Amino acid sequence: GPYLVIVEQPKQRGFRFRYGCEGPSHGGLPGASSEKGRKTYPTVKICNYEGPAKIEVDLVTHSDPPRAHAHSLVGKQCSELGICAVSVGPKDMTAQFNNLGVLHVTKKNMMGTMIQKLQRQRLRSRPQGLTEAEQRELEQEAKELKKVMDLSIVRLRFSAFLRSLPLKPVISQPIHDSKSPGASNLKISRMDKTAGSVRGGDEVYLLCDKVQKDDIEVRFYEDDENGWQAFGDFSPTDVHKQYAIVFRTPPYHKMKIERPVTVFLQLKRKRGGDVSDSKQFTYYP
Amino acid sequence: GPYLVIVEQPKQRGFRFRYGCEGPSHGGLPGASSEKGRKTYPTVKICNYEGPAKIEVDLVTHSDPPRAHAHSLVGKQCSELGICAVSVGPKDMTAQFNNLGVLHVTKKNMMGTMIQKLQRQRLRSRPQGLTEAEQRELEQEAKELKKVMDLSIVRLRFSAFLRSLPLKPVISQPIHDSKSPGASNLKISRMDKTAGSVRGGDEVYLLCDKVQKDDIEVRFYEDDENGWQAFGDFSPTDVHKQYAIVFRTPPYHKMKIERPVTVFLQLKRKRGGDVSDSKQFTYYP
DNA sequence: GGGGAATCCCC
DNA sequence: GGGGATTCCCC
């Protein structure tokens, strides 16, 4: 049957969710491959095409049975409820989502809009109103929905409709908030010293972009046909105000080196597997 | 005749102003000298006392003619408007204001809090109500009072009353909000190196509490019967995310030293003159 | 497109 | 009492 397929995924990291207060002109969610100059935007296509179509995009959660998220999509052809709906011409069955903004609901707002979604979703298929019992149960699956909803991760859902007749919804990979503390861009600004003894144990003052003291690591490594890794040693007290890490370097694997060796080091969040660009450190005999 | 005198002023820096949402039990505004184990609180005394008395404190602007601040005192024996009122016994004429807080008004709160204290002021000495014209001009103070009021600086105003009968009001020194980006205690957490060449030019990484790029300095000095002083060398790019300063040490005043010499360095505010606790640095040959 | 100010939550 | 997450602001 006709199916929709995502041809260019949204970029997983690097994009920021904006609050209402910020404005509408803040930059559209870019494709999974958008380096300098060549920028891409999420794109999908209806394959084995049947009848001029329609594609709708909305924000779902990260958890599995996809449910609508408190966040809303904003911008180019976006409805006041966070639904993006476009028409995919008779012949060209591909839609490029040029300008997708992600609206960040405040916690003192979630409850309200979560209910407006569930009402809109409930009085959707079935009839028009909600009796008092019905409006009470709504505020529970929004109170207990709040408690489990991750406001820093959303997924894009593409629901296509042939002229309406629904094609199975296709969900994209997760999109993380680049402003949220735990999904910020990792960067090594400056480093104290870039050389030390092979024994390791040299104290280093690395200045970096915000990190969370209990979710950050300084990984030293080298990549030949084998590979080696070690981690700078420090305590949570050593991460100064989220923007600096004071640590002792780890030992190199061979102690008996006759010449100085240069290895790579990067910041890494224990959980995410996310890393910073790499800097270098040289071990001395 | 009887007058009030501040026996122990409030501490000018390091105290945090709290918003209504944080809580009422976060600590009292301490005295000028409150190091580990023995804390003092602002204290005043009615010298050459006349009759048991009544002392009241409230927040006045930093601006000279002391006018009431939009911020209110919170805590022990404080009224819902931010006036603290106590009675000093027939004997001991000293009042130690043990638990005084500063409730921080939001910028969206300011106007309403301001027209409300201004109304209360109107129907103070003079008659009971406000005509619309009187209310329109009361709201006019509020707007033109907001535009020139520093929400980061307040002053305590002690008003003593002989049982009532007024005494002259005594205004304390400014009190800076430690949470305002530009008002806390300059503090040197730790630094890279504590020794370097008498030639000056050695790069030091200093970790500090939040500081302003363009309002900070690194003052080196040694106070004998002379007084040499010099400065760290760094550009605002060298002040990293307000929590670290990468600077190059200055040259010592005598290039010909034969024995190492210990001098001191300290962080200093440019447009203020307050310094952090000084750390030592030793110049070597 | 991004840094830092202002407000709030919480161990 | 303090650290940092959130929400907002404005260059």
Image (cartoon, coloured by chain):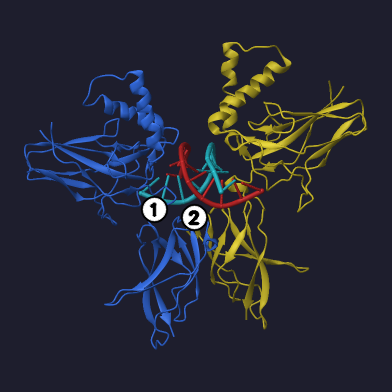
Chain colours: A yellow, B blue, C red, D cyan
Q: Which amino acid, mark 2?
A: Lys
Neighbours of disc 1 within 10 Å: few (<14), some (14-19), many (20+): some
Residue B101 is drawn in which quadrant? top left
For image coordinates 42% across by 32% down, the residue present is B109
Mark 2 residue element: loop
Disc 1 chain ID: B
Q: Where A207 sits versus B193, above or below?
A: above
Q: Is residue A151 visible?
A: no
Disc 2 chain ID: A
Q: Where B225 sits versus B113, above or below?
A: below
Q: Nearer the viewer, residue A284 or A16?
A: A16
Mark 1 residue element: loop
Q: Is residue B73 visible?
A: yes
Residue at label 1? B184
Q: Nearer the viewer, residue A149 or B227?
A: B227
Neighbours of disc 2 within 10 Å: few (<14), some (14-19), many (20+): many
- The quarter in which the C terminus of chain A is drawn is bottom right
C-alpha separation, residue under disc 2 versus residue under disc 1 = 15 Å
For image coordinates 68% across by 48% down, the residue present is A14
Mark carried by residue A151: none
Mark carried by residue A241: 2
For image coordinates 26% across by 55% down, the residue present is B33
Mark count: 2
Q: Where A218 sits versus B262, above or below?
A: above
Indicate the position of residue A275 as horizontal and vertical percent values: 66, 56
